[PDB]
Amino acid sequence: NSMDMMRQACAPKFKVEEAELHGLRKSIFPANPDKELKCYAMCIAQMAGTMTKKGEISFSKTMAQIEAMLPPEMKTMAKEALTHCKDTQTSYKDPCDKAYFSAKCAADFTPDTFMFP
Image (cartoon, rainbow, N blue to C red; front, side):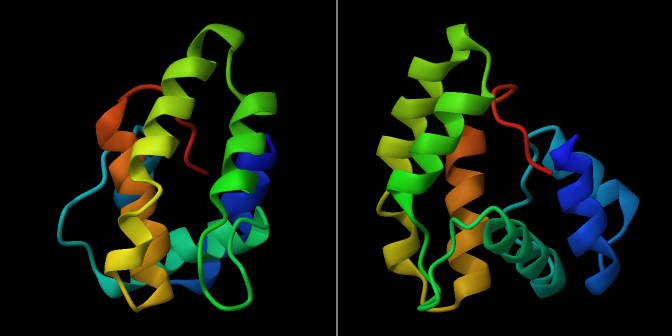
């Protein structure tokens, strides 16, 4: 898994622990997480290349990634979720918030669908 290779790259850098991370991997995103957990989600986005140097999330890149990565029969639902959640980042100034709440929006929209490293 480049999923586990992504978590392994980011996790040691943040004050996060296995229970938190297990939760995200299972599409469970608390509404009020530690800042460190939000910044872990940002680290993941950066490594996947979905975060722009200005600290915004690329919808077009995230969409392209789903298209190669998800089971064929999950793709339309995952695309609907990303489309719906596209604007979520625009309500947060902090780039850790943008990345974390973007993923939470998608995870909430269609549970048991996304793979969060």
